Length: 143
Length: 143
Length: 143
Length: 143
Ligand SMILES: [Mg+2]
Ligand SMILES: [Mg+2]
Ligand SMILES: [Mg+2]
Ligand SMILES: [Mg+2]
Ligand SMILES: [Mg+2]
Image: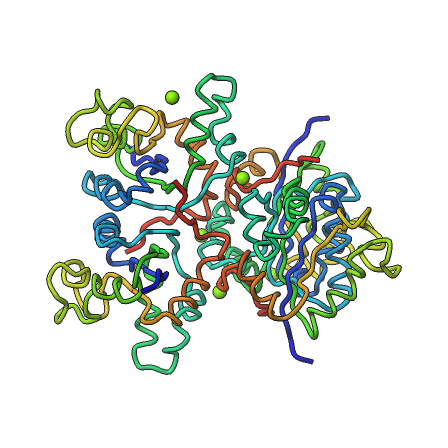
């Protein structure tokens, strides 16, 4: 319905196995538009900040450790119902529970190394996009 | 012989028609690694600076117009023989002579809108990479 | 007496007459901490996005033309009462009615070329800061 | 006479004591122009890359730690004889040895925490600027 934006991250597992293009392609094929993107290697601090709402959770240490083990691609995806449509083609967090032809089905090995991230809601998307991108970096389409 | 780095730009035609992933997946499949990437909307000054070598050429104005008409994706590709490897994946500058399975063959409408740019030599690749990317921004593979 | 963040811009006038340091020293003396900064040459699109609220005003053209005539310095100042504190240091918009020792009084040539910009409130500070800076780019103090 | 470019870093000590403006002022007072600047918090990798040349040396870890202890301001300074001229203003590497009126004599505690960095030579300034800045990111004066 309303055109929304969501944060994608191609996680270090998918980057190291050179699946960036294949994953971007799935998004584009579903009608999401890439309106920002950049490759970064997160520092400890950078990861902890992104995930600061899970700072006191037990899983934080290993999450942070994985997400800093190699470079990631961060991207803003734009489209009708983007938050959810993105989640649709990402599929379930567990690859074993993920539908066929989702990203988790096709590219994830495990729960921890599940290939990609999408924001879980419109409020999270707004915060997550602002964590990685100045609005000045987002590139609306003009052709 | 050696591992080289080269600059890729996805031009505004291919961005606008949501081919970023497909193009990227062609580089990755051929064994090139994406070690940096960002989307930008080039200003006139950004584009003239990049293309300064062609400043006295007939096509300069049209090139700068086209390259500033909407957002691009600039990337650093790394691999064995990457400069020329990337060039053969791209195919002929003119899409009418480009071999099948090349990016210009598959995604370019015309010589003017030819989907993507690749650095033409090692010396040129180093300047064009430096133009868009601080050395600190390129993300070597770890893991 | 709450810690806030606000946007500062050193305008192309003050940049071109090399008053960046002097200006920065005023803020630091008054207690504000510089937690993000960058020099940028704004494109017309960059400037039109920042000043979007004024897009229908007759002065928009002049404003955008001046804010893109040369490089600026964009910064995030943090401190107690940061928004209005920053404003008292800047002084009145018009230099002719700004109190001696304010930024406008000492560095502004005219109303149009009034040396610097400061956010006018908390809502606008948040919007302005986010326009130029990813949260990941802001550097909280660590010693 | 030859216009040169050199790298300035305001180190984590001078930042934390809010001396950035005071230091920039000295550069501009001396006729150097700030043509790029940013605040960053360097990670271990960022610093290891900058100081790669000294990596087998025995001060390397001590240097990497100090330079990651807090945020820094990295700048490109432009002017007549900028490398040597910048070096004169900084003063002797050891602030106990530094002439009065030099930023090391006036802001530096000790040889560990000497307040600012400067490129040593013209060949090294160019590598060091290229590490932190893309060519396109540096802002020549246009007004
Ligand atoms: Mg686990
Ligand atoms: Mg912009
Ligand atoms: Mg006027
Ligand atoms: Mg950060
Ligand atoms: Mg430029």
